[PDB]
Image (cartoon, rainbow over all chains, first blue to last red; front, side, top):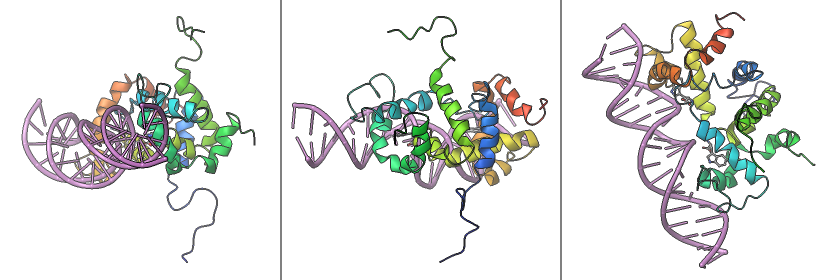
Length: 105
Length: 105
DNA sequence: TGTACTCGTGTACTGGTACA
DNA sequence: TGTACCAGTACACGAGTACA
Ligand SMILES: N[C@@H](Cc1c[nH]c2ccccc12)C(=O)O
Ligand SMILES: N[C@@H](Cc1c[nH]c2ccccc12)C(=O)O
């Protein structure tokens, strides 16, 4: 059993909250897409316009191969793979994610 | 019926904005990490750490130089891509980065 | 027969060398 | 001079296959 610097949410590999404070401080206005450029490949317009499009239906249909995740977008894998959402675990904090969507509780 | 996209239309690409306003709100704590991974790019948790960290230090003066780009974590193709990064932004969006470094604020 | 999951490839990442 | 291509890593984006 090794010791741990307090509990809180960030620990072991935090190095991210210092990232959000500046990443969103720009989000307030149109300064959310100026970060998807200074990094060259951040042209994730498809990795964002198509990936968000996967939960968009995963939280409603979640049937995979039936709407248009890839026939004209991109998700077939990024929409059916969502079944593995455990990777970024939604339920852990989906509680707030649903708060801004449904969180019917 | 129609998405009405003739003039302006909603907040322009609501797909990215809906993911920005929801981010900042949860970006305050760890409610954004579930989304940054289960709805953005999760293995990118390292990519963002290294994609901005290069621009972060780029404005400072390091993380790129036949040895900083590497010691940084993967800035070589990145540090160099950082130049191409201007591609997703004609020095305008990069201007927000300066807003928190030299532009003014 | 249908559908789900897993897999493929290109390249995110990571970093080295050569060229511009 | 540093990076862009290129090499490596392992994954992402994207594809296909297998089972039910
Ligand atoms: N996540 C960034 C990673 C990146 C690629 N090349 C870069 C150059 C500089 C900074 C970041 C990057 C992106 O989407 O591209
Ligand atoms: N970058 C995320 C995007 C993604 C791929 N497949 C998904 C399935 C569901 C939700 C998101 C995704 C990932 O690699 O996982």
